[PDB]
Amino acid sequence: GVLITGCGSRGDTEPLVALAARLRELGADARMCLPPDYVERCAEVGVPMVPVGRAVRAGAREPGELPPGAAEVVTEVVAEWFDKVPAAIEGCDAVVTTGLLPAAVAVRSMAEKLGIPYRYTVLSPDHLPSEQSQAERDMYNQGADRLFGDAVNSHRASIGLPPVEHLYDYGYTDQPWLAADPVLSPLRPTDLGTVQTGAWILPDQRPLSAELEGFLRAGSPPVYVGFGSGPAPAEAARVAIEAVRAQGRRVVLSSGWAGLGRIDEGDDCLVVGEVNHQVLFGRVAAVVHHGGAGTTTAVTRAGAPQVVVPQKADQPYYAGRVADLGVGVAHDGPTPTVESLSAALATALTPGIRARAAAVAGTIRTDGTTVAAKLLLEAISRAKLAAALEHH
Ligand SMILES: O=c1ccn([C@@H]2O[C@H](COP(=O)(O)OP(=O)(O)O[C@H]3O[C@H](CO)[C@@H](O)[C@H](O)[C@H]3F)[C@@H](O)[C@H]2O)c(=O)[nH]1
Image (cartoon, rainbow, N blue to C red; front, side, top):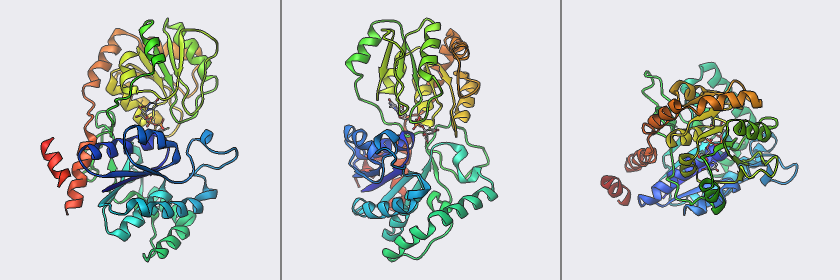
């Protein structure tokens, strides 16, 4: 089998589910360890998953219950991963991981014990160890060792392993994979070490809800607005609904983890939960979003013009990439006003940008999981999988 693990938000998780599903299609018994948020997602695509640790979404936890990434609970997190992974990793020939470092180091430790290959994956190039300075890498290693090195070493001893240090190096490996699209996220030409597979995208077969289908059929193509797993700006729903209205468009508002909702009973708005983005984004006039790696990838592949309203982290990078590609507008700042978002939307709604977005869509590859599957085949070899890939 192959074990696929991670602890993080939807963006950290969805690529892993894509890889797991692709491996199962290719005849490999891929299974997962993920936070409990993702039980439904894994089940609906037929991927076995074992829930590990605290829920990542605040609303999925108890009031006052700290997230898995909180420094206060790191000892508990390490223990939980060492407790639950053994049953899942048994009979596996390789492991692929992303996300939270203390969990990743636990997983690699168990891979080390079994003598099976471990691969860590990053989703945005700015997060590659080789894109950090030596001083930064030193700092990350020291912080990890200090914060949870003792806990990791106690559990390593429990299974007979020697102690380990430099936990950033250990968890990320010396050369993590980059599961990111090369058009959206080009790698510097001097980097010969990083294996860039392309994005890991699950071909989405889920139907749209009757309500969303009805909404799409009942009028002109709407604008989608959503902020993914992250926070939304102040008055996000009001500003977005009023700005989209100002452009003469209907609105599909994704509630997201922020829990956005309607501002009135207007029938020109539909509030949605989880949806098939691959299908929906082909049927909208534009997408206003936060600039998450996965969301940007999906919007770009669908060919919908964009307005990126970046909140934090790697999101300004994606806003800049979208602007540079000419397929959308990088909104100036994290908190739009009706006026600023309306202006950005007007720009994103031109025939020219529609054509540019349509053209760039065709350049985004969707076969990154096949690249990763072949890389795994080669790592394990050093059957059904080899036969399936030869067929491809
Ligand atoms: O209704 C829905 C909602 C989502 N999806 C899919 O979930 C994926 C979300 O990916 P994304 O990377 O934007 O995740 P997110 O957790 O919001 O963002 C961060 O995690 C990212 C990765 O680390 C990071 O780039 C960023 O800064 C984050 F905040 C993407 O493939 C969507 O198309 C869906 O199919 N239907």
